[PDB]
Length: 125
Length: 125
Image (tube, rainbow over all chains, first blue to last red; front, side, top):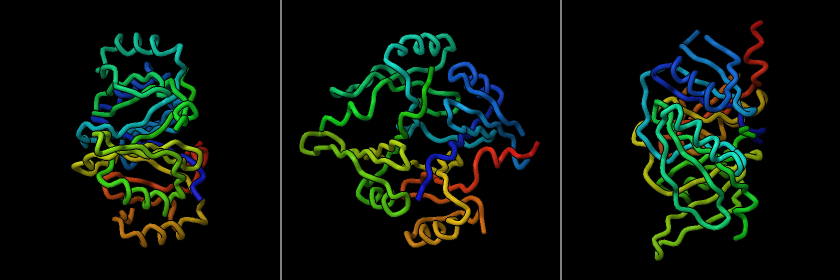
């Protein structure tokens, strides 16, 4: 059986610029630096994230990872995002029981979500 | 502060096919299903995999394959097993015994099953 999540790997054109983005917004903790290729490992809220430098670029889509935050934190995270001038999506339509979320991109078409809801709340079906 | 992973969202062209894929390889557990075509409401399902909340929505598949990917953890003893398990589903596998397995679903998503922990990966001290 699957024990759980091992890690998430992302490809970016500029590793040092992405590093700063991760360290600033997600308080990412760099735990490794290159090797087969140029890469860095970060710990983000317990999750092992791998960033590799490459010219590969996925077209933008709703395929994304979302991190858990608290409702009372949506505004502060919003100010933080605006400050770095990163691109933010507008309010997405949602149903009752679906908490607030903010969406923004990195520099390589990676959509990230900060969700203030709980799976339990969305199970009023 | 970001407390952790909320969920992972994947867009697929055919949920039924993808569902079976998730069930056969990851023992994915379906816990939610919505959608109503006569009401112009696209379908989506929520799955639990080794405790992780995974969301699937119907839409276009990635139009190209990249190295960005999600890696799930397993045991070294289970590598040969999953290798065969995945081969039996007929999906493409990257030959890249063994410590890590790479393969695509039906929508150009690259998955990895990885044996070994973060600690193990960074033992070089």
